[PDB]
Image 1 (spheres, chains in turn brown, orange):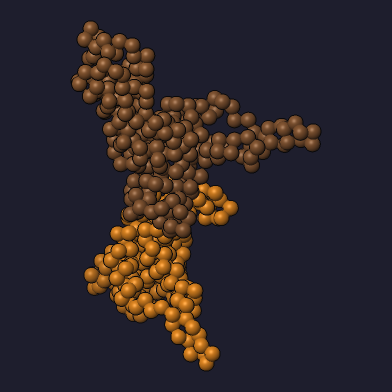
Image 2 (cartoon, rainbow over the protein chains, first blue to last red; image 1 turned 135 degrees about the vertical axis):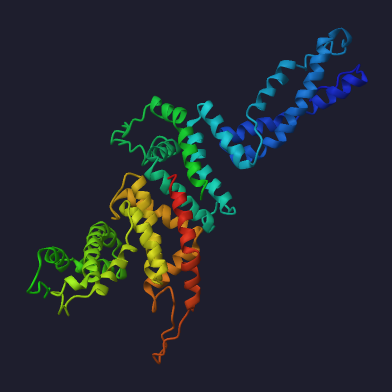
Length: 227
Length: 227
């Protein structure tokens, strides 16, 4: 924001004025909508960011060139407000981006939720994605209970999950309500010393999500394919 | 029953005593359990009848031989209690018989319910067969509401049918309750002159069952295959 330094040459200012206006707050919002699980908006933003970083690549490439020939850019002489590392590290988001329909983009978002050990979101996404997949092949329909193509189509995924992947449903619901739930059944106590009802250790969830949650998902979607 | 005539030669009596004891009442029970829709018992009996008719073929073949050389069988001289046509016509049931697992045998029974224009049973069978198909691939389970593998597995077929083959469900239920139902909604009248609510003509049902009911069924089972 506080850029645009005094002595400026045409070619450097043309590159710098692009960099100055890099929409970094979008990449922040993208990460926020992922941490707080807003795939609908997180996945939608993917195409815009694909344009943001493509421009940030060809901008940084020029800056890399100017700093690789620093002897000609002694206007950048006192630039305490500029950092090539701050920008180059923002380029990492190119990994979190893929191409395809919003459904295909969410399928990728699942794997990102698995690699980053954010289990809660990974399971919830793997649970609701097959609903959306089926809605696409039945002509499409809103995620409202009023919509019949949703209502039935959600019962197909709920019932298939509940008789086959009995664990997917438990693990999802357990993580969704976390502590103090009908899923965990703690005793609470007259004294106030809450005592847990179930256990489900760190390396219970860890193994399931990180080793089977992907394999299981592909087996669900391959079933709903011929729907 | 009133067979075993007086002057009898060893070879004719050996064939005739087999014929005399042909279990025709089984073929009757088989047809009864089909007309009144007892596939569970109708399909089970298929293997027994496959043995009945195989013996009735090689019995009639000997009788055909004896009657093709009538000049040597003048003991059959007065046989008013014997009829080759009565037996040969019972051989037709070989068509109503196929080989395979009881599930595969029922899949054939569907087509027999379609060729014979007995719609009511055809639709009901095409509705419940995919439940049984899914139960087989989930390890198997009783057709009781207490059984979880049934409960969920029936919801998969009900929900898939209700959002895709909306007609399969209507036509089945309409024929199941027939006249005077929540499916037909007649007004009844204060006078007592019942007035119909819907129509659904002879050639409405006729076209659906006889032209699409088979194609639609195969599309359902190909979906539940990867379950």
